[PDB]
Length: 130
Ligand SMILES: O=C1Cc2ccc(Br)cc2N1
Ligand SMILES: [Cl-]
Image 1 (cartoon, rainbow, N blue to C red):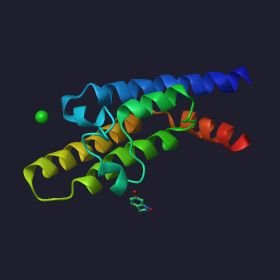
Image 2 (image 1 turned 135 degrees about the horizontal axis):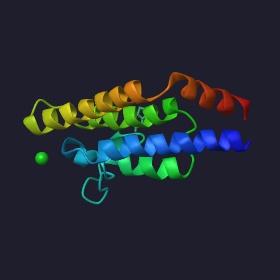
Image 3 (image 1 turned 90 degrees about the vertical axis):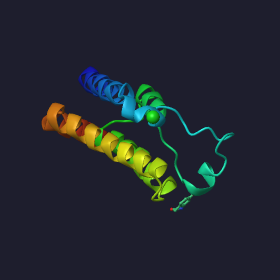
Image 4 (image 1 turned 60 degrees about the vertical axis):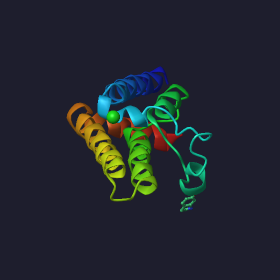
């Protein structure tokens, strides 16, 4: 229905706005672009599903997210991948892990404040109907 297509357009507007606000934060710069496989060829041999904020933006636009739960699965991957690939005690690794955790915490706090639970419930009921 046009009502349902209006619902998903509003979801995509909301997801673009959250993602833009994560992407412009100086702490999250390293998560805005894919890991360069030339300059880091080991990444793909040890991380199963790479994710970054530029790939989240592409997926919003290709209509890959039909719920906020689906979007948060990708934000969680950005964080868990950073923790996996940079596990050591050196300051370079500790700083990346601190910034990865702050990304996930910031995304969850925006959504907690700004997402209406009835709007997410409607997205879920339309998704389960298809
Ligand atoms: O589920 C797993 C664990 C894992 C880590 C990394 C890569 Br690449 C593939 C897999 N398979
Ligand atoms: Cl820096």
